[PDB]
Length: 5
Length: 304
Ligand SMILES: [Mg+2]
Image 1 (tube, protein in one colour):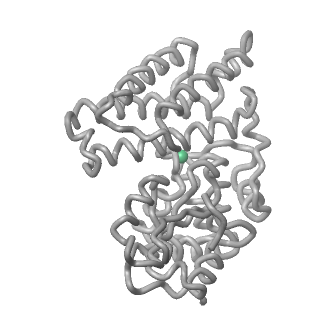
Image 2 (tube, each protein chain N blue to C red):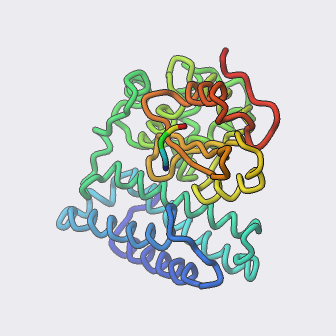
Image 3 (cartoon, each protein chain N blue to C red):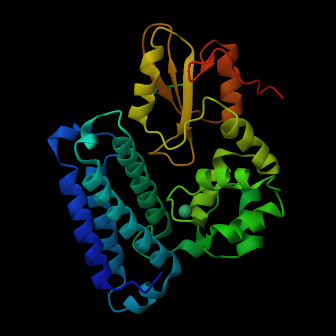
């Protein structure tokens, strides 16, 4: 999971 | 569900052992990523081993616990169902887009949800279901008023109690609701499953309106999908930036995971924090990231 765009 | 004794847990351990062996077949090309059945079954065995160790000399208390009887009944049914799936699917278990393989993936998710529930109710091997913390105050008040300190209730009892506060418009809607909330697929609703649903579809005041807008009529919602299935499903949209889908996080139960195709050729997944899913989807549309739900040209209007 990656930070929100 | 009958009384659970030490012999019954050993029978489930043998059945889980057969499932593990079936899932070690190199033809499956099983990826080591959650939900990973080769981790979940040994971890379930270890937690059951922990539970049994806390109830030495008081196995009569453990055997009478209603939640634990329902859990062990479901664990035996789910492992038997996985064994039968391999027996009937034969070579179709190894075709990555086949229905029997998809059934195995859904079962892997169910084993993950079951282990999460078991750890939420028996956090250190001892039953704590009566003091479980429902994370939204209004939802906690509903469960307390309707069911007191119970840990698990049959679907029928739950539907009736919910309908008195949040009317359910039809039998088909009730079946869609059941399919959403019953993560362990056992025809019961645990206080843990209720917490997850009410956190995902908050606020409580508009619970079923939220669930209808985010799941029942939204083409972006994906029930019982894994991280790897989301990446695979978005591949066909790699040249269509803004295509997106969303689903329950497997490893952070109660939180949402949104997968989307970026304008630079990547497929990313994110877990919104400190904002509800509807606002993440609205902001994502306005900022150009979440435009095409499941690759479709029309996006639902949630600003309403
Ligand atoms: Mg259930």
